Image: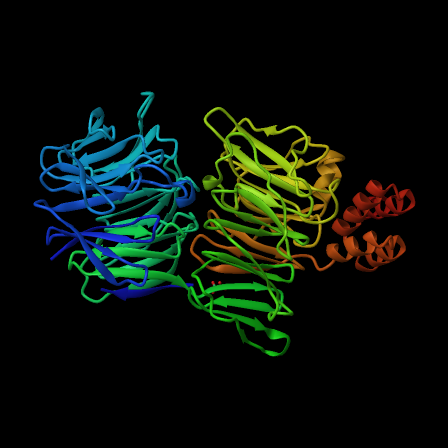
Length: 633
Ligand SMILES: O=C([O-])C(=O)[O-]
């Protein structure tokens, strides 16, 4: 994918509302409205004041919108902070700072407004403009502030440093030196908890919430002047001197675009649906970017989302391409798998059998789709109104799993996982981190919710077999990898120093990054049975280093595709044999499996077969396998 860019003294601030209007604040002392086509529509207001920053009152869903929430706040150079309506009516003007107010953000729950001054103060206000508290007084201008999602913590920069402070508690403000120079912008994703920064050392960087560096860019020619997370948390944008870059959440860049005489891009804002962004530059021009050329593939099928109207389906059964009919509303979310293509527009969900593109099943959407997941039998669609929805591939809603205190706007693909019989959801709260399971038939809770002692980074369900086969992996914040069956549910630790893990597409096998090495478990369940045989069915490629923070993108057939932190996709061969053993054994062909193992004389396959045999209680076979293993010793 890439950023498709369109360009419209200084344009000081930009911000999209949930109605997909872009408001821009310029040094002409005017505020203008723009539409998603990147066209100017109206002068909304004119003020005797210069602008530095703006923020729309945050709305989780325009469907659950009702209230006086159609307002935005603007920071001014005279130190005032003004709340304006969508129509430009001044609701409230606040004398917030001495000298310019240079950054501000509404809390996510809308109960507070945070402002920061060149005077180095960070202040917290009620909407009534009352001073709620002075959070901080730094020794340098606080160029950028953002909230934690719970609104009990604020992240801000001062000098070279990033600071995280609690509003309620005191404890210890976490702080670190982020850049070798002045930090110019920060952002903190509420959905993936990652922090991004850019500054005068001419780099951008990605951090976790604890100050651990996850990515640092090479040198730009000039300071990085803005960074912004897409609401999806899967992408962020970077602005600089006549440049705009689109980055993966891992940090590496999809595209770097040179802009036409914009000066530095000082301000960034994304649309709520993460498909577009806007940037304000020192020149005063407004830049519009659209995320395009999304590529999906599954087996022989390749799908390219050309733009928000146009999709091509490439069916390489004979080097083919089919252009889908142009979409009547903007394409928002697309997913491919299991022989089906799902296209969610702003108002409709299309489900295509990829072999019969001419007859999709289509149903109405009443809210913005925020996630699509697919399994063999059905798929999952998420929005912030009805929440978690499980659909047949003919478009019939099967169930709507829910639980008290579920916050759907915080779920990404790391937090919720689907399979043929089970859904698992990470329920993250100040009180506790627990994994909750639900069945896909009725959406009813399955078993007792599982509590971990540490914060969890991500969870994922295995795909093969039945409910008794269903397993969850858990990676926690210490980078420990756990295995947890849905039904027997007794946890086991599989690895330390785990950066990633992925279930095999078609079998119970598991892959993971373990201290930067590729490790494969041919039979992960063995950990509950026999630690010694578990080790014999676990293979680590000792000499292949995937670097820091590598992410497994696919584990299927006999290959594992691994995305490195630097954006390089590595293809690693795994054993050609264990999937064949799985196939043979589900067909009860124990004779054939023993013959195969006798032919390849591979101790790890003998161990895998022995594990399979013991679980099936094929004792004759297990005996042969153990005999073969003990023989090579
Ligand atoms: O996505 C890819 O294959 C790449 O990195 O070129």
